[PDB]
Amino acid sequence: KETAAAKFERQHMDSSTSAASSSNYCNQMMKSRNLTKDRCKPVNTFVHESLADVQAVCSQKNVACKNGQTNCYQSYSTMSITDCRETGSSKYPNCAYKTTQANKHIIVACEG
Amino acid sequence: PYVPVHFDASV
Image (cartoon, rainbow over all chains, first blue to last red; front, side, top):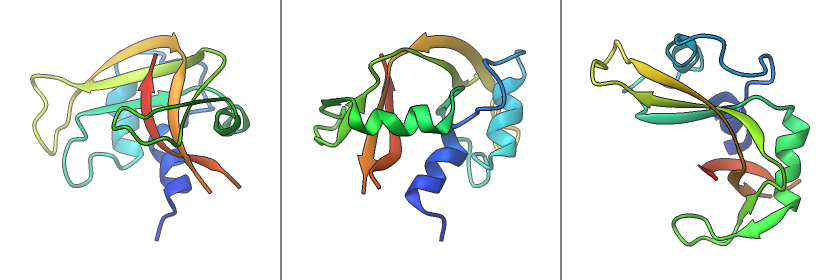
């Protein structure tokens, strides 16, 4: 089965672009990454950085996850990210998203 | 190795 690490890359990594290039980015990426297969994932974030840079977050600032778990880490640096959020017109299987470009610190959960 | 398995939030 797909590993949790591999699932992370598929759902959130986009090292081939520096940032979302058009309003259609979310629509295209959510579809192509198979995130809309069973239902419309309501929210999703893509990171436009090298995988190594994102993997290094696991050795940066240790913080509590939103749910209280203690294996979260916050990037020391801000990263180029794209926020994908479902639109009022979204209706499975024609999932629709609004694309929002940003530069912020990311918080990931790490395992090993 | 210790790698990211979940995206928790952007701050």
